[PDB]
Image 1 (cartoon, each protein chain N blue to C red):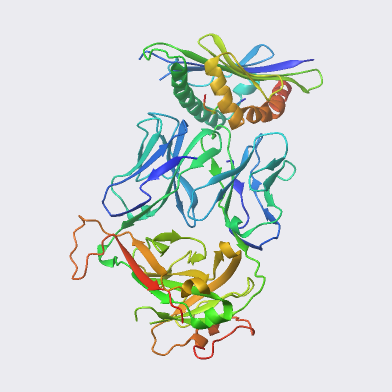
Image 2 (image 1 turned 135 degrees about the horizontal axis):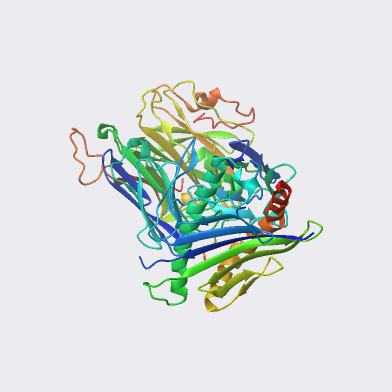
Length: 240
Length: 173
Length: 9
Length: 205
C-alpha cells in the first residue's frame, strides 16, 4: 500500500523548476508517473522497469524522470508550463496490470501572478428555525475570491479536525464565467445536533489552506502578496 | 499425431547490457531465432511460411523484445542479490515456455520455467497452479508469483493461445 | 509466438 | 491496438440498487483484465483482476466481474450499492508485449444517491457570525435537483450530501448567496423545481 508522493501540493510560475518525488517500500521494479485531467483520464508520462532504467510514456514532452534507486522515482519539470497544471500520480508494480498508486500531487503552474488572490473566509451561524424544526444545526462556510483554484477546506471543532457531518462542494464556482482567469468561490457545511451547537463552550473553525506564491517570487502589486497561507473564520455555540 | 512447441530465451550479463537470445521450435524444428550479437539484431524466421510475413509484424515482435530485454537486465540483478554474487561476473538467466498437445488437439502439458547459471531455478508444475522452487532464492520468487497470480496468468496462455498457435502453424505447413 | 514475461523475480 | 471501452462517463443510482458498469474490450487472446476504483481525493485501487479460470471474479467490497469471451465483455457488478461506493471506476486491459504498461478506460463516475427516509424540504437563512447573508436549501430528497441562478449575480452550489454517522443520518444541501441589496431567501431557489412541500420559516422566509 505504501507508495508515497511528495509534495502533495505545489504551486510555481511558468519557467520554474518542479520536482515531484515518489517512494515505494514494496520492492517493486516498475514505477510510473501519470497525470490526470478532466477530459483525458489517466495519461502516462514516464516509467521504469527498475533501478537505472527510464522508459518514455505517452505524453513525456516537457518532463524528465530519474530512477536513481530501486525505491525512488522522480518527475522533473525543468521549465514548467501552464499546460502542466494538473494532478500527478505515482505507481509501483511487480506484475502486469497490477499497479499500486500513491496519493496525488496537485500542481498549479501560474502564467500571470497579477491574477492570484487568497480566499476570504466567512462562517455563517445555524438558522434558529432549523434548530427548532429539525433538532439539528447546520453551519455554512464560504471561501471566496481566490485564484488559483488551489485550496483545501477543513472543519475544526475544539482543536480537532472533524469529518462526520461535513460536505464540501466537490467543484468550485467561477465568480465570473466570462473572464477566463476568474477567481473562485467554494462552500461547505458542517451539521451537528442542536444540543451540541447550543453548548457555548463549543468552538467552530472553518480553515482554508491557500496554496499561492512563494517567499521568493517577486511581487509588484499595490496589494498584499497573495502568498501561501491559512485563512479561517470562527464561531462559538449559543444556547438561545 | 502428437505435437510440441517450445520457445527459449537466455540473457547473459556482461562484465562490460546483457546478451539476449531466443529460439523457437515446433516439433523439434527451429522456426525462428534471435541474437543481439549479429550486426543487425533482427528475428530470423527459419521456415517458409513465416518468412512470408509483413515487416510491421516483425516490428511489433521486435518492440516486445526490447521490453523483455529490459526485464532480463533488471531481474538478472535481482538474482545476483539473492545469491550474494560478485557484481563483476558473468551470469545467465534462461527461460523456457511451451506446450505439448496430444493426438486429439487437447493440451497435454504446459511449460513455464527458469534456470539460473545452469541450475534449475523455478518451474510451473503440470497442474499449472503451483511452482516448484529449487532453493531458498527460488521460494522467494515463488511467494511473489503465488501472491501476484503468475501461474494463472500463464495458464491462460498455455491452455489457449499456445495451443491455438501451434495449430495454425502446423496447418500453415 | 509470444508470451512475454514480466513478473518480478 | 488493444483498447478497452466504457460506454458512460457519468452514472447515477440509488442506495440499495444493483450496479452494472459496462466494459468492452478490443479483441485479444488471451485477455488480461482489471477494474480499478478511485475514491474522491485518492489514487487508484485495484478492485479485481482476471487472468484465467473462473470467469466470475470476486473483488473486495462485494464487487465482482464477469469475463465474457462471447461478448468481449468484462462487466463490473455489485448487488446492493451503499453511498460510500460513490467513486470513479476504471476498466483496464494489460496488453501482451505492451505488458509493462497498463492501458486504462476513460473512467466511469458513479454517484450513489442516498435514500432519504423522512424528507423535510426547507429553506432556512443563516447570518454572518461577524457581520452578510446566505440562503440554505436543505433536507430535500434524492430526486429533487437544484439548478443554477439565471441571475448571474446570485451564486448557487450543487447538492452536497453530508452524513452524521454517529446518528446514522444523511441529508442533501444547496447553498445560495448574493449581496444584491435586493435578494431574499424565498426568491433564491425559485429558479428550481422545489417541492410544494418545502418549509419556509416565516420571519426569514
